[PDB]
Length: 171
Length: 176
Image 1 (cartoon, rainbow over the protein chains, first blue to last red):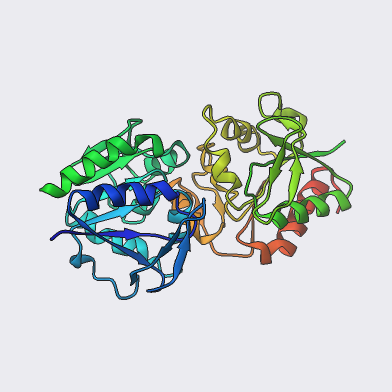
Image 2: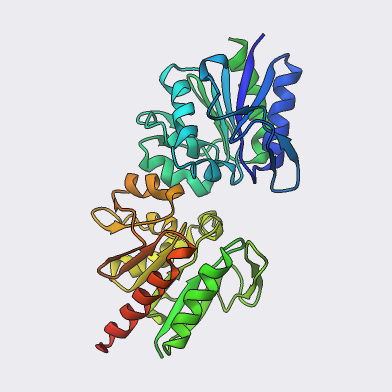
């Protein structure tokens, strides 16, 4: 069975967590929440409460068949980690071309891999300049697939994002 | 009239607005909040309400003698402006070397000017990588002054931040 890591902090955009989660689980895939502490709770922008499954210190990126990065301000919180552990976690995925899914602000965490030069990505407008300065070819589309990396911009894009992410995992 | 523009959206970090504002106003300078629509309210992370003085469609950066950018998630919101009008607004201050003050996340808007290459600043950890990628020399200090650009990291830096921003405005008119 295939298993998706979801990196999450406080102030995720609720639907960007729950909608891709549902779509993966409907297609028969497992999901697991990676966060600061096992059994700590993080709370979405609109009050959705999520329990962290696995602490970032313990997580073994090789256990996972994909990485999902929900947007809102969760990615900005994650980039506050004083040891940069979420970027380092995400680097396993970009370095080994493991399916990597990021919506809205989510691709902020990808910047910290240093792996974006020459890659084609979209994101929420707020973050596009920073993605470009990280070396990405940034476009403005509802969903972008660049080999293993699937990105979308906003919650309106979810239908497209969700289709493309479960497809990528079927391989 | 030496007037400081403050670009502000929702979810600014309250005291990064109120403390610098007070220090500027104590030192005799006026402040003008610039936002999406004039006479609307924006609300801090901890619920401070601030009225927007001037709409960003109306604002002329010429009118002002400094630019102050409070942090929190206000700068991120401002970067979601569809036409990028707050980056454009800030481009005047960076191009013409006008006093430019930013704390925490605040330097994110300075990235949109494309004027950061070779400049030296600090910011909250979360945005340091993005400043580097924009070509800035990023350091970790309580306050950094690079000619006209004043930056700090976090709320505990405010005593240092506020000293330097007022000192920029005083020196602008040769008072020592």
